[PDB]
Amino acid sequence: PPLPYAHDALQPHISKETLEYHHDKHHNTYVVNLNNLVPGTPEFEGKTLEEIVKSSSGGIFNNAAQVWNHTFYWNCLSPDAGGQPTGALADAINAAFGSFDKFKEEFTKTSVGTFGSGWAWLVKADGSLALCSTIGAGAPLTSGDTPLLTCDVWEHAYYIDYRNLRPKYVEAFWNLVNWAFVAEEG
Amino acid sequence: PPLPYAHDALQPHISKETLEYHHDKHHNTYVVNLNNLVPGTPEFEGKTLEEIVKSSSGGIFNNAAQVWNHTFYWNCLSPDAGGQPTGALADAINAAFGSFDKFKEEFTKTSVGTFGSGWAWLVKADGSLALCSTIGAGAPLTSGDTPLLTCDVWEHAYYIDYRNLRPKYVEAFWNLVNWAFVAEEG
Ligand SMILES: [Fe+3]
Ligand SMILES: [Fe+3]
């Protein structure tokens, strides 16, 4: 039942049509985890969203999963954005992937190539793993790991390209900042 | 090896840049099939129509399923509208789905309720009722039902309506294939 957003608005090249339609795809609906849900019919009452995954129902009560995934997404982004360094996480990826061009050109067979909707992610169990999970009802926080970066590849995460749309993750999304917010290592 | 369509990209309920993109999402995009068919082996070299759905274990391979769900659908929408099943077809619904008024308002459910990408399908086995197929390239053909009334619920199914799936289908898509070959002869 939150009201995320800030840092962005017009966020360079991913529009305000797409963004405050999409920021609302997440918080008009999704923030639906409550109505004839939490309080409403399927239970859980005292939870943190963080606490929804692991314990909770299924897909219907995994719209609550959508809220986390999205307000996560929104803090993983651009508008002052760029490419890794600033420490060990640099060095992490650089020996797991081995490189970053490599990292960015692998983290796609994550994203691009997953039949349907969901999100690709940068994850860490106790060292890094690039995890598929494209179903919506996929947050690697169900298991023994926690996400460094996400990307909604659900068809409305984008559209501003339409006949031929990969340049969405590429020629649209690698102007991702919060390499400072993705900086996570433990 | 598909190149056809029942009419030209619409006009009044489903745009021209719906039928452009959706039909080629279908086309030169779902060309993934032909890429991994005879080429190496699978046992899918031969096997009639999409007998590759029934045998097939998908995603990239259950592309077969997707060629099909899309070609199924094509026939399902026609400029010739009339949410009026004659009364041969009318019978098998005006006894199952309450009535037809009550079939539609029940096909809504399954269609909007298919959580992110998927379908709402009207089948027949030798036990009758509707169907929600929420996992991607779906299809009732592995289960073995065999009339079919399609739809498409993927977000690419609507550049029109934006987030408004229902206005799109429980609205717009009551322009079903004149219940003649929806009307069953097999
Ligand atoms: Fe989204
Ligand atoms: Fe489709």
Image (cartoon, coloured by chain):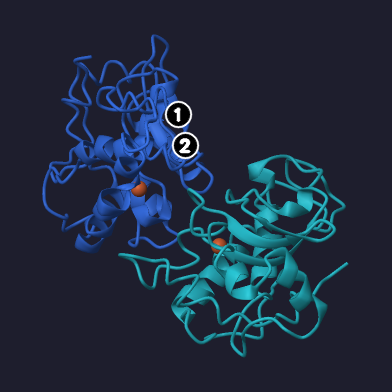
Chain colours: A cyan, B blue
Rendered position, A47 above or below B94: below
Front residue of A58 and A31: A58
Q: Residue at x 64, y 82 (%)?
A: A83
Rendered position, A137 above or below A172: above
Which dot marks residue A47?
none
Disc 2 is placed on an element classified as helix
Q: Which amino acid type corresponds to the residue marked 2 in the rendered image?
A: Thr
Rendered position, B155 above or below A159: above
Rendered position, B147 above or below A114: above
Which dot marks residue B110?
2
Left or right, B54 with reference to A63: left
Q: Give the residue pinned by disc 1.
A: B131
Dot 2 or dot 1, earlier in sequence:
2
**Percent position of residue B121, x then y:** 39, 31
Query: Is disc 1 on the same chain as disc 2?
Result: yes
Which of the image's four quarters has the C terminus of chain A?
bottom right
Quarter residue B67 falls in: top left
Q: Are marks 2 and 1 in contact (CB under 8 Å)?
A: yes
Front residue of B154 and A124: A124
Which of the image's four quarters has the N terminus of chain A?
bottom right
**Percent position of residue A99, x then y:** 65, 72
